[PDB]
Image (cartoon, coloured by chain):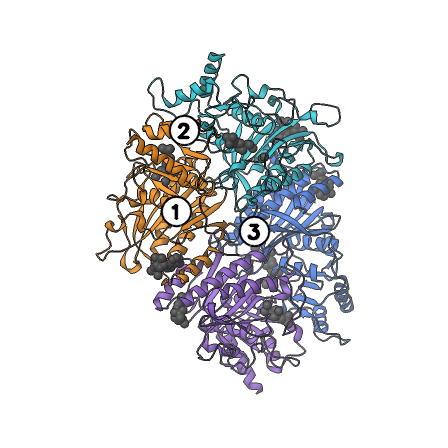
Chain colours: A orange, B cyan, C purple, D blue
Amino acid sequence: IVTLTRFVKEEGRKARGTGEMTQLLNSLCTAVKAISTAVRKAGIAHLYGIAGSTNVTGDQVKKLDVLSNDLVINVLKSSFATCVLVSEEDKNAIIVEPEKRGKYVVCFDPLDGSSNIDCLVSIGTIFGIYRKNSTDEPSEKDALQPGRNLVAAGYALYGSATMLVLAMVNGVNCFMLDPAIGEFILVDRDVKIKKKGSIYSINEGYAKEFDPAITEYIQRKKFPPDNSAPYGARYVGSMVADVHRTLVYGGIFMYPANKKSPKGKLRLLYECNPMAYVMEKAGGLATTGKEAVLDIVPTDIHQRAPIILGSPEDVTELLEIYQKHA
Amino acid sequence: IVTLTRFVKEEGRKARGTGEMTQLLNSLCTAVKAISTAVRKAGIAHLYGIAGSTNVTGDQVKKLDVLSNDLVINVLKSSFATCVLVSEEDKNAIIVEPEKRGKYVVCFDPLDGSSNIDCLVSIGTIFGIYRKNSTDEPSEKDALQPGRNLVAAGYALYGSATMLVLAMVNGVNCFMLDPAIGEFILVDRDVKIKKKGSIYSINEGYAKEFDPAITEYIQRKKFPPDNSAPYGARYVGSMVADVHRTLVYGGIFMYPANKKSPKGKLRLLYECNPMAYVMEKAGGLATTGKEAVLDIVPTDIHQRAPIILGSPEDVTELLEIYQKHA
Amino acid sequence: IVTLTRFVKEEGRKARGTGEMTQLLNSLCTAVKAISTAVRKAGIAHLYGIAGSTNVTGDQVKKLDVLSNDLVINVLKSSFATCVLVSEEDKNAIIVEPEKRGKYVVCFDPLDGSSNIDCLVSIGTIFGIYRKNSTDEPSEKDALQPGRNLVAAGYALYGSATMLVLAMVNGVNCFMLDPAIGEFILVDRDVKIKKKGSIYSINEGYAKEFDPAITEYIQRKKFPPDNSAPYGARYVGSMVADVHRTLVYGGIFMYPANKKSPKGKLRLLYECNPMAYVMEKAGGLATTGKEAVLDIVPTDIHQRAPIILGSPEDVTELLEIYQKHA
Amino acid sequence: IVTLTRFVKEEGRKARGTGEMTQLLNSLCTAVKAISTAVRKAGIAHLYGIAGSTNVTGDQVKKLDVLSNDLVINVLKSSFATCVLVSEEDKNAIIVEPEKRGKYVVCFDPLDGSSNIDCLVSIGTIFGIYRKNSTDEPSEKDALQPGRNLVAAGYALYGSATMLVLAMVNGVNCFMLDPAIGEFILVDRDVKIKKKGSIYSINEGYAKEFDPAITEYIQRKKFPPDNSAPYGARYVGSMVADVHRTLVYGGIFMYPANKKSPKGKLRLLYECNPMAYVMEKAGGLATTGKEAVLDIVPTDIHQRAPIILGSPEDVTELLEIYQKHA
Ligand SMILES: Nc1ncnc2c1ncn2[C@@H]1O[C@H](COP(=O)(O)O)[C@@H](O)[C@H]1O
Ligand SMILES: Nc1ncnc2c1ncn2[C@@H]1O[C@H](COP(=O)(O)O)[C@@H](O)[C@H]1O
Ligand SMILES: Nc1ncnc2c1ncn2[C@@H]1O[C@H](COP(=O)(O)O)[C@@H](O)[C@H]1O
Ligand SMILES: Nc1ncnc2c1ncn2[C@@H]1O[C@H](COP(=O)(O)O)[C@@H](O)[C@H]1O
Ligand SMILES: O=P(O)(O)OC[C@H]1O[C@](O)(CO)[C@@H](O)[C@@H]1O
Ligand SMILES: O=P(O)(O)OC[C@H]1O[C@](O)(CO)[C@@H](O)[C@@H]1O
Ligand SMILES: O=P(O)(O)OC[C@H]1O[C@](O)(CO)[C@@H](O)[C@@H]1O
Ligand SMILES: O=P(O)(O)OC[C@H]1O[C@](O)(CO)[C@@H](O)[C@@H]1O
Ligand SMILES: [Mg+2]
Ligand SMILES: [Mg+2]
Ligand SMILES: [Mg+2]
Ligand SMILES: [Mg+2]
Ligand SMILES: [Mg+2]
Ligand SMILES: [Mg+2]
Ligand SMILES: [Mg+2]
Ligand SMILES: [Mg+2]
Ligand SMILES: [Mg+2]
Ligand SMILES: [Mg+2]
Ligand SMILES: [Mg+2]
Ligand SMILES: [Mg+2]
């Protein structure tokens, strides 16, 4: 019955919004559809395999990384709502030219999941939207804000279906793409994560490098102290994919710092922050183990951060272990 | 350039085949396309949520389980090539009626991945094809054969793309579905798995129940004895999904027996056997830890079995640990 | 390169428009896509065959007539831009409720071509947009304006491809629907009709009822006075279809009054007016034979009118014959 | 419920056929789907506009003409059922190479409707299938047979929907393409044309060149002798399109010889013959005005012929006028 487009427009009314934010969200979706479609046939269009350059964070980049980076920059440019872009794949910040310039700042991972592209596992797109407070000209700085300033955030999952997850001050709603008429249809409204769950998601290959808090916690998941049944384990290897299962199943997801990565591996602007926002707006929690992720003031558009999120009873348990070892 | 249909037909020539096996493979694909399509929009068509009955193996069944079971039975019936069907969801064997009866025996998991349906993670279809040796009437027995008698086997993956993996005596080929013209297009011909890999896939929540061989092996993956870097870890929760990554990445996949499941959890006819066939035809190995899976003579259409597969240097390593503890 | 959505938005800028007119045009397209899709498979979804009621103009109505009437009313309602609707299929005017009310008046033939639905010949949608001048409450009257007040007009053709033809004060542009990503892509910008053409389109079965001007004109088409080759003849039976060929080929289209239909058969609000607007904005002409169609002040939302349009040298020729017989 | 593929296979059984004819029909459909898809987006893929060469019959050829010619030759080649091809666009006959050679002879208009390509009006594909009687090597001669030897014939219509019309000795059935799963679904089984109808289809621009029989007949359509209401008139300009409306509506279609075209304009092998077969198998009639079309022995693969077909009471009426003037 309800399309995204109806929903967003109506929300926009309720908010009295002028319309900038709404064209912006519509430009984005269209971008997502464009990607879903490329993605569902990459091999036939021979989009697997690398393009060439490595990237600021040392990521080998491949043709899909680029193709989807471009659609997006380009669709945001032409939205006429954004003055500053931030891309996984882009070394410095993109300052939109004046004629198309607006007052929104959008950070994004055009394609998360690089590992799983070739083996056809779920992939996605991550984005965050901040509003330019400042009055100086639109420099890079304007994209250095703590997540708590996010006005909107979400991700697209290209899993067994394509889905858009969007979250704003009100709450979280899930829309699915009808491949048939090319429109997103709302399927879940105002979702909330379970208070406690059954699954722990973490890459255990790093067992060697984990700190003693994570180590203990994992142990506690596998040998419950109280005899309850033990937690099940899932790690896909795509954040968007693991985070999503966690939103709708409950449980907890983990990419904490390690001996060799004091700040963990995920990127704070365009990975960590959006997900923690979503998680919190759904009734989730999202910490580094020492601080809430949204409260970190960024000093590099490309910086990394530890991320632990999901059901709040589950997250809490780890935080207490963390303090214990303090 | 090359469609499935061209390929199969040509193979059929090279084989001098009469044509039964080829209509059979074509009936199947069509079934897969039918499913992919339902699947990419289940939520819009409201196919998430359960149907009602539990199943012989105690599986909660849900609407997609059924919808895809039916398309398939029905498309195989009408292939005119099969005399005996075996379904995850079907209590006893389906004996095809004479008028449509043929000489092939097909076992199948219409939908593997039940956990991940609601969270939109990759799902698939598994199948095996045996040829009826016997001359008695077509009873259930005829589907009790060791995998080594498989004439064809494979799976469909509904991941970020839909893909058909088919394997016959010659070798393994991968085809992808062009959503646009509704035909499968061959993308990889005569694939082979790497001899040794970087990833171990297993549900570690069972850490408590593993035997001492698996335990040691996991330990050896996380703390290499020789200082090489440690293996990475992936478990999606969909066999088809994990097995596929393993075929194209190398590495190893594991659902071994545990303290509470002496024979492991995966089903030998319609899960274990096809995958081990594929794996071996690709240059893989597939054991219970004590015997090759294909060599087990089945005595129940619905029986379970331990399954360890993937790169042969990787599989070997575990077998030696297994013998060690012998 | 350019989507509809980019185009319209940009036009809207150039026009300084507040945004109402632009959400309105976007709501409409979406409606068109919805229809194209139903239409390309009506038979499979069993949309051929009648619904039940006859209609104000005595039209037998059938399931597609309804299905597309509804999508449209509903998508216009929710546009939040329109206060008064006019439907082929609707007896009296639809007054939008206040909460969704806007300042646009849209008349429309949800589905033109009824004859050719069952035989799968081209069908289309016609629409006109007027802006409410008045300050009284939004009654029906507000949709009684001469075409010259149209702020926008066009049609969708579901021919061998789906196409959107839109025309505003600037000129005419053609967009095509990419079935694949579900977006309209501009293919022809700022089109203009040829000054004189080779084709006459008219239903000659009415030969008996034509007046002496049309009769003479047809004769002159078949036996040129100057020996030039004779004009070719096309009548599909779908106005949208015939009018479109005429825009891009040149020539002339005819549904003039007859002995038994003093005012011809096509409906002025939602058929005649949009087409004449398009035609004129493309450099065409559009007369009853006695007056320009756009200049007629309507007194019934459902009234009929003669319509002759196309290349201006061609139209002129008939007008002179018309005056001759004056 | 029923797909083409089920239908054809079953028919094939009833016929005891070996299977050649059935792979052949399946190869063809696939070709049709390929075309429908190109066609529904030609403009976006920029397939409008000419390729270059003129053709044996003096036809300006354009990119779609070629693209669809190729898919088809190629898909028939690889069917392994055909030894001799005949193309609108091909100067001499295509003799299939031995390795792929079979025993069927297929004549075809890869794309009928050239006029209406640019204006997006309905277009189609026409084909005829003959079986090679002869024992000499497969030369061109083998495609010179009277239509009565056709074992199968039909056309694809890319109208507001794509449809396959197939006719064999049994009768005629209509299938529609589900754009969504890419399979043809049977919608009308064993169709029959009305005995008498309301519509005459002919290009009246040739009024000057018609003979006295056609002239009188048209006159009789416009001024009934008995006062019945007069017939309506439709000519789209695409044979496939006009012929189809005639099959399902009744009436009559006309491209008779004229003063300047003693043998009319349509091509006997790949246009005239298939349509007359269909028409007759549906309970239709199909004459030149002097002889049945199917009974003409062809002497040039590219020859032309007059064609008059449709409801038998309607066709008869003209034949009597023809004899009258004898
Ligand atoms: N479509 C919308 N959905 C939710 N909030 C909106 C929308 N449009 C405007 N707003 C609210 O109004 C603010 C400014 O939007 P804008 O009017 O484009 O500047 C945003 O930060 C939103 O919180
Ligand atoms: N399309 C095909 N692809 C591969 N092998 C085939 C094919 N058709 C027939 N064969 C071989 O011939 C055997 C019998 O097939 P059939 O002729 O249908 O009984 C199969 O076990 C295949 O090994
Ligand atoms: N997207 C647009 N395209 C063309 N003209 C527009 C557009 N938006 C606004 N306008 C012009 O501004 C007028 C009022 O539009 P609105 O601002 O919605 O009331 C219309 O009559 C148009 O002529
Ligand atoms: N699928 C089919 N549908 C209708 N007739 C068929 C079919 N297959 C075979 N036949 C009949 O058998 C003849 C030879 O076909 P084949 O067995 O391929 O040589 C044809 O002329 C048909 O009349
Ligand atoms: O393989 P690793 O080191 O566990 O990291 C995987 C992570 O990296 C990412 O590809 C982002 O770079 C995520 O999608 C995923 O969660
Ligand atoms: O959650 P578990 O117990 O690890 O089992 C998951 C397995 O079960 C299955 O759903 C098959 O029943 C597989 O797809 C998957 O590998
Ligand atoms: O069959 P007639 O009387 O010529 O009218 C056909 C016309 O009627 C319509 O269906 C509109 O009612 C047009 O699409 C078409 O041009
Ligand atoms: O424009 P004409 O001379 O009437 O011929 C149109 C005919 O030519 C064709 O394009 C075939 O060449 C047919 O589709 C159509 O019926
Ligand atoms: Mg990267
Ligand atoms: Mg990325
Ligand atoms: Mg990423
Ligand atoms: Mg189950
Ligand atoms: Mg299953
Ligand atoms: Mg399973
Ligand atoms: Mg009507
Ligand atoms: Mg209508
Ligand atoms: Mg109409
Ligand atoms: Mg030609
Ligand atoms: Mg042609
Ligand atoms: Mg033709």
Residue type beneath disc 3: Ser
Residue flagged by tag 1: what amino acid is it? Val
Query: Which residue is at 46% across, 60% downward?
Result: C175
Q: Nearer the viewer, residue B96 or A188?
A: A188
Q: Nearer the viewer, residue B313 or D4?
A: B313
The extreme left residue here reads A136
Residue that mark 2 sits on:
A220
Callouts 3 and 1 on one subunit: no
Residue in view at x 60 percent, y 19 percent: B296
Residue that carries the numbered disc 1 in the rendered image: A278
Q: In the displayed structure, would residue D311 be above or below residue A173?
A: below
Towards the viewer: C31 or C218: C31
Chain for disc number 2: A
Label 1 lies in ligand 11 vicinity (Cβ under 8 Å): no
Q: Position of residue D70 (x, y in %)?
A: 54, 46
Residue D36's disc number? 3
Alpha carbon separation for disc pair 3 and 1: 43 Å
Drawn side of residue B126 relative to residue B235, left or right: right
In front of the other: D302 or A225: A225
Q: Ligand 19: does it lie within 8 Å of the C-beta at label 3?
A: no
| A24 left or right, relative to C159 | left
